[PDB]
Amino acid sequence: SKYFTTNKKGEIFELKAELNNEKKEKRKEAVKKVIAAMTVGKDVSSLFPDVVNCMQTDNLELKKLVYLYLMNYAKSQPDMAIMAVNSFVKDCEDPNPLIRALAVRTMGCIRVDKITEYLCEPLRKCLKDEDPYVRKTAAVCVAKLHDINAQMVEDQGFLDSLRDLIADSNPMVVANAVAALSEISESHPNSNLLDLNPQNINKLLTALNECTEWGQIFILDCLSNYNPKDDREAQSICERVTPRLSHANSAVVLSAVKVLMKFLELLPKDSDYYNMLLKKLAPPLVTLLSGEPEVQYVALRNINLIVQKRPEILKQEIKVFFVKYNDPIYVKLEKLDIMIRLASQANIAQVLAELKEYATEVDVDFVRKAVRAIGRCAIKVEQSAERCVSTLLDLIQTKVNYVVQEAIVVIRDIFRKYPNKYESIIATLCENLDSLDEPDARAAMIWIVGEYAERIDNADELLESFLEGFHDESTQVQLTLLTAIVKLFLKKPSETQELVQQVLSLATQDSDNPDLRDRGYIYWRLLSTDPVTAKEVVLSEKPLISEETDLIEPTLLDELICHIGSLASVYHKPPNAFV
Amino acid sequence: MIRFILIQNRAGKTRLAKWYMQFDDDEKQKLIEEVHAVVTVRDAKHTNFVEFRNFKIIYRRYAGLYFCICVDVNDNNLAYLEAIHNFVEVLNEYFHNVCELDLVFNFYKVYTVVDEMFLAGEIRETSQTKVLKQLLMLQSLE
Amino acid sequence: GMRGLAVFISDIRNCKSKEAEIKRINKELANIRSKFKGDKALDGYSKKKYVCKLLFIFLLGHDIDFGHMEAVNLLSSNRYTEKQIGYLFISVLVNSNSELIRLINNAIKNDLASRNPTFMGLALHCIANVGSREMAEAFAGEIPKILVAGDTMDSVKQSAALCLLRLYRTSPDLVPMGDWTSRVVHLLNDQHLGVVTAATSLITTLAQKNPEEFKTSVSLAVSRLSRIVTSASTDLQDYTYYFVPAPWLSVKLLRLLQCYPPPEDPAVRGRLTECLETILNKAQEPPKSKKVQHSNAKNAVLFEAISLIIHHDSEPNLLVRACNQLGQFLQHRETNLRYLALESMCTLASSEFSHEAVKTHIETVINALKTERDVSVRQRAVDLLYAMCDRSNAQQIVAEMLSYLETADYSIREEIVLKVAILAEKYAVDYTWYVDTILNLIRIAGDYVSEEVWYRVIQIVINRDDVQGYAAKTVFEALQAPACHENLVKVGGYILGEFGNLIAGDPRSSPLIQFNLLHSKFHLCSVPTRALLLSTYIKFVNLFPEVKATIQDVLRSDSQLKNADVELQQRAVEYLRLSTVASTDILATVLEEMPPFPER
Amino acid sequence: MIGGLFIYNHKGEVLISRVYRDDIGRNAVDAFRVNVIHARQQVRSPVTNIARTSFFHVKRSNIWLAAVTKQNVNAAMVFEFLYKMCDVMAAYFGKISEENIKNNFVLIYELLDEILDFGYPQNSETGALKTFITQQGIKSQIGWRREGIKYRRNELFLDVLESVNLLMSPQGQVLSAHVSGRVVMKSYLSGMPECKFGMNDKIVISIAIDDCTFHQCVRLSRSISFIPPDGEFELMRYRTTKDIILPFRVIPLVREVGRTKLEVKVVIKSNFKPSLLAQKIEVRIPTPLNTSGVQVICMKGKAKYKASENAIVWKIKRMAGMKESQISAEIELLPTNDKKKWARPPISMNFEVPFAPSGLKVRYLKVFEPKLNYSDHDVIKWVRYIGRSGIYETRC
Ligand SMILES: O=P(O)(O)O[C@H]1[C@H](OP(=O)(O)O)[C@@H](OP(=O)(O)O)[C@H](OP(=O)(O)O)[C@@H](OP(=O)(O)O)[C@H]1OP(=O)(O)O
């Protein structure tokens, strides 16, 4: 019922006496204990008048503590926090700049209807203040109000009031009007952040240098939004940004990189500005892969893009993207990926002595992605595919089951970009007919015995061994069994009649896969029909594939290179997936 | 039968724990944890009954406190659900508007009350009048 | 009482860190170990507080590896409070030390052998609580004697009964059925309902393996229940809880009676029926209080009687009334009553005298599920529908299962999609019901539909086709949600591939439109599904030679031929080649109507 | 910008938090507890998007720090901040642990309203911060491998051997589950090589308790390092109870048609990646003592009723992931014992699976012998995962 709720004794009644004791070092303690309480989920709502009364103080720690408490009620239950607006108001006038800032920020974190009446004017007064810490708040709090409903005409006042303090003396202050503004501007009527520009640009790229870690970053971001028109406009902006191989190891660099690359449309190299820039951009990226793991990941997810658009930049620096045994799987994968993309026609020497390293390590997922990477390699550089296929044999003879199976599947894709060139090896691959438990590996063999059928006189009792447990088989293994036992009949008869019966038997009659049924039929409607015209639709030349997959749509590439810093650069997806 | 009775605050702290089955201390500590994870995560809308390991739990909360009985699967939910409430009124009477700190500072008394109402994993005495009468006689002894 | 205890507790509380806390605890342990080891005697008050402080620390987690001897001395005190604290310590920290057990066992002998009910109480509780073999061996024989003696207080008999119950559970072999049987049963007539309760719990456990021995309790239990459920408001005021007269005793009495078949003596069985109908009546009577505690006590008794009725499974009129009353709980604020009603109705559905009773409430069940928030209540709504579904119901039930599915949360889909497939198959009178069900099933919840099920549909469609152009339109007007999902594309790209013809004439479902639509799915699908569409797509040039050119240029394209995959690269090559090369009578001899299945 | 900061303990209980923008309710927290803190077969990354909400996070000891928005935020920003929050924090109270978080609720709140206004990484270096933060953090502080072992060929094998246990209701509630495991190591390595071993998070370091014991050779300080015994030995033993991957669900449908027939249909679902094969599958569906006989039907594997067993036994050689399969039986009952409901024994399974139901993954084993001539690149290394049923039971 209301059992255990009494407030005539217990912990709450105790704290109530403590919040009224006239020894402030005991009041302070109470309010620590109360804040403690909220966080563990207790109902301190009944102590509210008593906590509020503790603001009637000289003491700063004590006022600051009451504030922390009211702030807990801010998003939590907004109503509660409102009950003491009549104290935020006549509490942004006090001296101590610390207190003024403290009371403004708090009001802006409240969200109900009656927040406007009391916040309007005292924010008008806060943006005009001797202390940059109070304008630095007043600033960020303009944003806050924007969220609670209203295009607010006076807000047109504020909307401007932000602008005018972008030409402010403090970089903490400015770089904050900006970050405030640049997000205000993503609720878009068509003209905002509006352009007093050469000033906007000139006074920002000076804020940018005396700035903090974080002031830099949101500035760099506001830039890239704007479009220049001329060479020397772009040029000068870029040299000013350039010193950003700097502080925030990672967001600072990559917001620099963002800018230096929207403004990469120039008359390049009559004189070589273009060629200095692209030289410059090598080192700072490079050094990100020495920072923290998480950030390495974002940086790598950005290098990925970057390296599709301007593959010049890191052409020479394949060395940083080498796998360190102790990195996280997710930083191992994104590296491997870029190791293929920068995989030139030269380095494949070492790149391959690396991928052989990994494919023999103890992390299974990564070993599989290694051997596949050794396919990606050979199918993007033929001046090496030969050495690949050798590398792959090494591993197949080391016997590690999961290394063998991944190795075979790559061998096929390799037997297909470079057809009729590695026919010798087939018997080395058939040594290991034994232990291909995985279903992909099998369909890799079967298709191998599929083409190159005549090169093995023993290609017969190979296929017969699989028919035993013909079910128990991935349907993709049977699809591969069928196409490959009619690649065998369009050549060898009579010895094959033993089987091509028992086989096509099941695709059309036993198996219930209606897609298998269709493809089984289609065939019987060719072979047990006409021995010549079956050939020309089936053994028809497969065209040479190219390196089809790993590569992004260049329209989309551009858009994402404009988002270099953000989430879109991690997901590789336009924003509108996550509105 | 009742396997154990816990009283527990939101924050996971045990204020009473009574076992009626053989368990090691680790296992006890484990169970008190498991019970907390299940019960704090359920909002007023859920039932007061929930299957737990190979038994079940009836619980209700009062202010910051979850009262829980773990009982056999075939035991009558609503009987136990109201045993909990019958026990809390006696507690309320016996401490005069009971609060949590009552249970902390008089924890050894709390086991007197439990033992009056529960024993050998069964409801013992259900009348609030008789239990009070006995508790107040017990209090006045030396 | 113990200021030193209160202060320790408050200091523990005032601690601003698990470190500070641990420091104050060790300080205490140091102090207690001195004073126990020390030379100045402790007066009782101190042994009492310090033993109590160690119990407290135990209950915070930490280890207590001493104090037991000081707690055991408290058993031998003549001060209640000292004894209590002592009995609590050994009840919570049970130590195996073969010595201390002996001394505890003496302390029990003396408190039992006293004749002070309080000390008998602590003693008997300690026994119930720990209940160690050695304790059973010391006292298992004596407890019955205390339980039946003409002179022991009621409170003591209550406690003896349950202690006796504990020892029988822990050590049956020490609790043979001696000469106390009839006097235990006799306690069921006591005036003191607490004693009646205690005795009923004990006898119940005892009836399990010893029914015949306690055969006599049936009649006594019946006469007592019925006296309880009929008594007025000025009767049993002690045991009256929110206007429900002795609810826990009533529940216990209906539970004792579940150890036995219907009373054998016809009068008795009569009485019990008056009883059961009196309880059932009371269910229909409106509340005497708006406090949920009242309905809960009344419904405790209602539910247990309902269990007694099921277990007897011998009074059809009571079973029907039970169902109908459960039937009315399905529409109820209380999630608790909904849950229990649905549960208890699943039991009734498997029973002859009650299956058709339960059917009566389908409407109510389908309407509660439809509106129900709680997941576990939903689950049981569905479990019940499954349990009542027969030839009559199947179409109703399946229809609503599918209706529910379109807006159903994710938690539930899997279980429902499963029951549907199954009910469809056990019951559908005619091939054509099935197909209408499975295609919708797949349109709404196909990513949960088995392999067999989307296969096995089309293993049967063959033998009675005549809805190939239903299948097609549904598949199609399904496919043209900017929503629709994978197994739809699989069976929908299959259906239209094979008979799009019966709907390519309809002009807003043309061949070109059909195609483009499939191809609005293509580049989001899997490969064995692109496998299908790269076969679908070729049957299309044949039936529809009107759009052969738009087909041909998706096959020749890069993404189809230079496709990483074996099948995609194999099919996009082969099929481009079948539509360009050979003849057209050779085209038609390849993507024809599809020769049909056998029967297993 | 940043929509929420949440510090969670290892249980995934939100210790302390602050929502900075109102588009992030109860929904965000449980999202992040469910799909990250208690991830199962999910591919970890530092960022994840679920129901249009993005999630950044750092792990520190037993703590999770987590940043959240519904916006196209500055990816690199968020992380750097979280690194410096962890700089700052440690400059008040040392480690980043539950304990230290627990003691410093009021400090932590204070830093947050300073380090991070509305979501924008505001000024926040240690000494720069004194001026605005009034509070003070509360601080708190061989004989198993003879010498001269030589092998032409330096090899090592690791076997992760796990037993997965389950009791589950008919509705699919995990009532209890636990895994028991060990890493068996078999190594033929010259010399006295020190090994450096790495794995994922999954192990921290009749009522099952989480525990992990090591071989005497193991040193702890991240990772595990040791000079192994030669040949075969047990590196670590453990038991775990959170975040187990139940390879199969068993969905029972037992319907008592009266007191004479009994309809039992049972469906099992393989809940692991499709490319992996589970083997040696048995399902054991019990039957009551008074059963004339049984008509069983199934279209995967083979099944037979066994009278002395009082059970139907259904066997399946292989089942890959993300498949379903179904047995149906029709049972026939002669009802002597008039009364006493049949108390159903659970359905149990056997199976074998080529991964760890605990989630354990071996990430590295680095070998370094100082004196002798060989290098980890030289060492041949096989891992295997055998996961096995223990008592894996579903009520029906
Ligand atoms: O044995 P001592 O060191 O002489 O002091 C104790 C101690 O007093 P303090 O707590 O102020 O140190 C007791 O509290 P505990 O830490 O032992 O629990 C207190 O006990 P009570 O508050 O329960 O009475 C007891 O008082 P007393 O011995 O009069 O019962 C008192 O001994 P002193 O009389 O010497 O101060």
Image (tube, coloured by chain):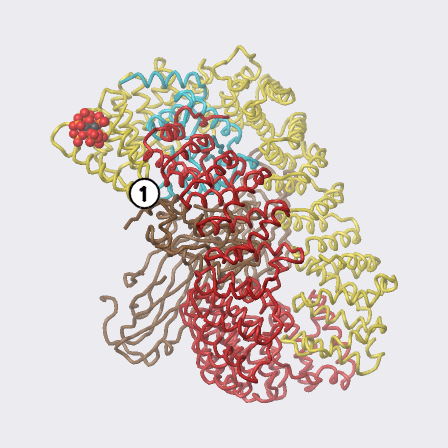
Chain colours: A red, B cyan, C yellow, D brown
Q: Residue at x 62, y 57 (%)?
A: A192
Secondary structure state at the residue bearing disc 1: loop
Please give left or right for residue B137 compared with residue D263 in the image: left
On the question of residue D362 being in view, the answer is: no
| Percent of width and height locating residue D182 | 38, 60
Q: Nearer the viewer, residue C393 or D214?
A: D214
Q: Is residue A548 above or below residue C66?
A: below
How crowded pointer 1 is (Cα within 10 Å; few <14, some 14-19, many 20+) is rated as: some
The picture quadrant where one finds residue D261 is: top right
Farthest residue to the left: give it. Answer: C39
| Percent of width and height locating residue A295 | 46, 64
Q: Is residue B6 above or below residue A561?
A: above
| Percent of width and height locating residue C171 | 36, 33
Please give left or right for residue D134 compared with residue C470 in the image: left
On the question of residue A438 being in view, the answer is: yes
Instruction: Give the quadrant of the C terminus of chain D.
Output: top right
| Amino acid type, callout 1 | Ser
Please give left or right for residue A49 compared with residue A440 in the image: left
Please give the chain letter of the residue carrying mark 1.
Answer: C
Q: Is residue D211 above or below residue C395?
A: below
Q: Nearer the viewer, residue D347 or C434?
A: C434
Label 1: which residue? Answer: C17
Farthest residue to the top: give it. Answer: C234
| Percent of width and height locating residue A44 | 45, 33
Q: Nearer the viewer, residue A304 or D21?
A: D21
Tally of marks: 1
